[PDB]
Image (cartoon, rainbow, N blue to C red; front, side, top):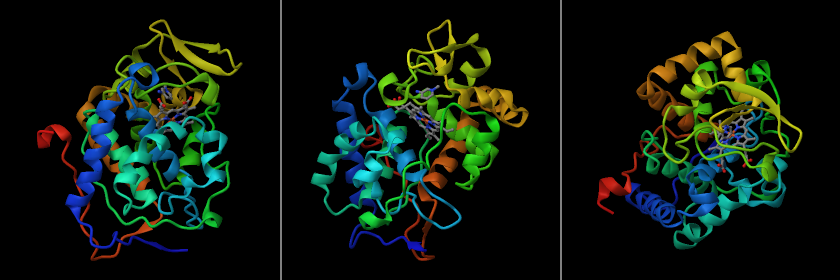
Length: 291
Ligand code: HEM
Ligand SMILES: CN1C=C(N)C=CC1
């Protein structure tokens, strides 16, 4: 199965910058969502979950086909709460009907990271909607109750190595867990709608206590009112992961650079870009455009 990127007919960088700008203006407007967090975090999670169904062994899933629009994937228990991000993007798709679903969902995540003062994430267009029968079955996204070995095995299905895993997990500074979505509750830190290396700092510097939550699941809780999933905490239990967590806690710039590469890789897994496709786009923030 090969998925060749095909540029939306006649569209260039400026067209996609307009879609980025619409997303970013709506992010700015809808600032009350989820007790004033805004939609940035859920859009990052959306872009990851539409990408994270990929299987390197047969090229099923991944961001290319935009299959999250189909009920089987939209209703995956692993995706509970992402309907909020889908609803946010609907008026954007209405304004730009020519964009593919996979391009829109992935661009949502890129826009969110940059508008939250994160690193620039290069982004490529050309994902093409595929039919309902190409929707991956549920069960391809990761469980949170597991250990470092599980995390490493899981991410190898996505061709991600240790550094890429640790860098991607830093997105868990953003937003929060919600008991009714996932059976976990709480934020990972204080700055949860600005992109920083706080996840790593908190892992290393907080006084964590293993507790059961109100859904009877184990999570690690700090006196500051932060939480970590067992899979997050595993990054300081595994010696290889711990070394990288320390690196990113010490150097936010290095974290930014590694996250940008890993996040682009995640969103492009499964896609063959023809050698004459456009170079990756780097979108200007609203601030950079005076908008
Ligand atoms: C071992 C891998 C991972 C596991 C087990 C995991 C698990 C979870 C869980 C259980 C939630 C809470 C969902 C809810 O209650 O609303 C969550 C939220 C989140 N996840 Fe992850 N995650 C993983 C990796 C990632 C990656 C790779 C990214 C993106 C780079 C990411 C980005 C986020 C974001 C931004 C949120 C907050 C969403 C919001 O505030 O609505 N996660 N994750
Ligand atoms: C520590 N974590 C924080 C989030 N916001 C989501 C998942 C885990």
